[PDB]
Length: 335
Length: 151
Image (cartoon, rainbow over all chains, first blue to last red; front, side, top):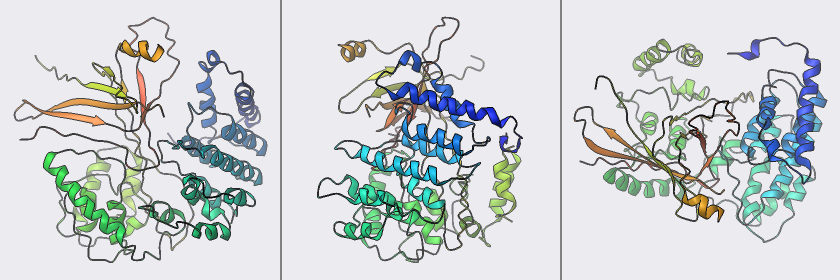
């Protein structure tokens, strides 16, 4: 259902409801004394309240109140930073974001950065967890957040370990120029990648130089994977991809090299980008691009010479489904 | 013998740094889910191809049994990953013969239970356990299929 449409009433007191949940969490988890016999009760309803809030309003008091605890007092066992991140936008879906929340969230990101600086910590989640998500998001609100002094307190380091060396790559757009200066002091970019993040927030388009070794070695060491994979037989669909991320680059006109049709093999999505006029049509699927990004896909589905089968794909899916998404897709960008 | 489609699955669990083995004989529910839905972004910059698609592809796994085993209560009594090795099979509709074996293995998976069973009849108590596949910040760490049935 589209709860967003429905109207609201008695907003006054539910504000005290949520501030009460917040203060309850603060009091319970704040001291050394934590009762798990208490943890087995409504801990869950506490998250349940922190959710259906979007679809509900929030003055500065209530929104500040939820953010203090949400960034400060919830135990990690039921909470990873990824689902935290996901939860904080949807609170900001139905309201604005004042200086206060900027302040608090920046405090969170810096001291949580200070939390992970450890020989072992890997900062795991089921999203990937680069609170460069946070950096870019705060950048998305307002014009700029140069990170004031938190920039400097993140710069102040030494030879040490390698953790912050690439970790600070998360928050560069929320940093000063001296950040890039003493980054250039050691080890600019060697990550086999860099695209994953730089292309995500800062670089994106307009310049994709001769990066040389990256894609070439990708193909060089993936041909042997192809051989030893199709010969023996395994098919894992492990969630990490760059062949598709460059196949989409190929027809996006960002990549104009002639060395793209090489692999053949698997990932019929790659064939889908790179093989217009002979593509295997007995692989119809409402996926890949169905994960419809926006207009890049208007150009994707331009395809003056191939439309006739995709319109029957729309037939098959929209006709045999009540899901609103697929027909909302069908109408405009496929017209 | 009329309409009795019913199969079986074997599921194993292991924590890292040691050859752990917690297992179940069956998984009655074995619900696998794949949910994908994007965010609300309206940056609106013309010279900015988005091509975001997705890179999360969350998984959901569930098993049920009466087995916590017995020996790990022993020793274990005396992130903490809970890696899982599935074991299932497939059949050819043409031949309906035993020819294929299916494996599923993860390097980052953690359990996620709802600690409120509290149900008002003491039932057979098939302690349903809900799972979650976690992802590190290194690479990959998703699956391994070990497709068999070579021929």
